[PDB]
Length: 250
Image (cartoon, rainbow, N blue to C red):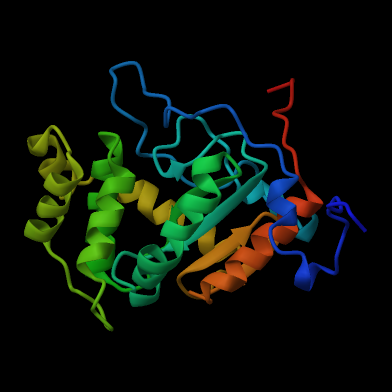
């Protein structure tokens, strides 16, 4: 033939990026999370969009909450990735350092995927302290930057870094947190105790048994699996659900 064929459907194992190329990017929430009245952000956000009662409710884990400082990407992206993670976990660090940046480049930056963080501290006192510090950073709109700085500092650590207050403060500075007095206070006091307890209870109610864990659209993935696996699941989910429209009733 003296023509360029239009792409036709292939078995999913050889479909490449057909899913994402046919998907419709989200156009809302591109400027990040919506602030509270005082200009800060709601760092008490956790949990699902709605209670899950059965496997049919799997999409309920994705909040799509425009006020959520723990989310990156369009609030109306056609695919959401819900992540359960621990700041002391080396598999969580590896996913953040090695997999997340390609997902940002290929999908999140294009409006195709939203990634939402959920706390699941499994590693004891340093993990809980890190999660409190993460919420303190989120209150000032710097969660993603704080998270990236913390995990970058763990890039060569095969165990737990055992981070403490001075470490969290450095990551906050790296992240550009403006009010360090508020950060240091909220990273240590009772501000986020209740929400962190509730977030852990929520994850345990789903049966999440280790970190990191992901719900990619409708599919569960446990652990820092190879980047290529996340890509295949993302492409499959985007082929199945190429568009998202916020319900008018909301």
